Image (cartoon, rainbow, N blue to C red; front, side, top):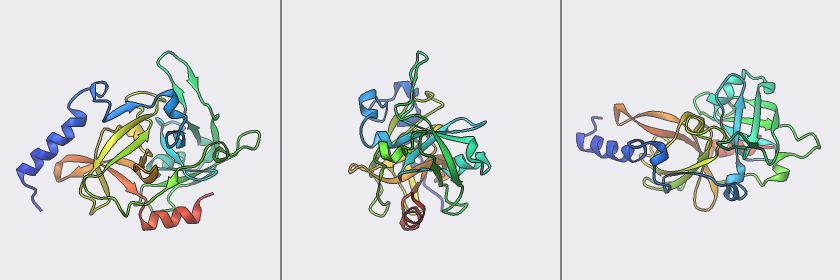
Length: 243
């Protein structure tokens, strides 16, 4: 299917809203740092930084009492070794050398590297409770798990995660706009690779997908964001495996 030059031009112009200026110069409506008070509330408080030994850190979402959803491509670098992964919910490192971890840093008990299949870029990370026996989901309500079934082309959603290449250990939100949904979640929006595993939320605060990567779009020379929606299969597996 040859896409028309007109459609390519429309795509380039829309994509350029997010990438045509420096990320620091983006309008706050499209991309902004989550401030200290906002990190305290839902859904931002479900978002954490996934550290994997030898890799730059990425994002994950607390979805159960001890369970974090992230990308398979992020979890795979642990080589199945839970000692190589840690989860830092609402970590914030300011620009002046101070890190806060209001809920502590969580060790990992088990990695489910590909419970949705190798071609579905999602992984489950099961956390140990803290040293006093307190699970992360005891301190914070996990994200409400929604569905991708009601999403439509043009829908605006909120993507929340840790855009490492832009700022290290600083939660940011990005407004995304869904496009062509026939092949899964694709969307306009500002992301960087640390956003892998970011939560995508609707206005009701329901998790409807997880950011994955960028993929070619329309032709081989253009691209779009891709995420994994909480579709019928993904929701079924989450409900089987969550804890």
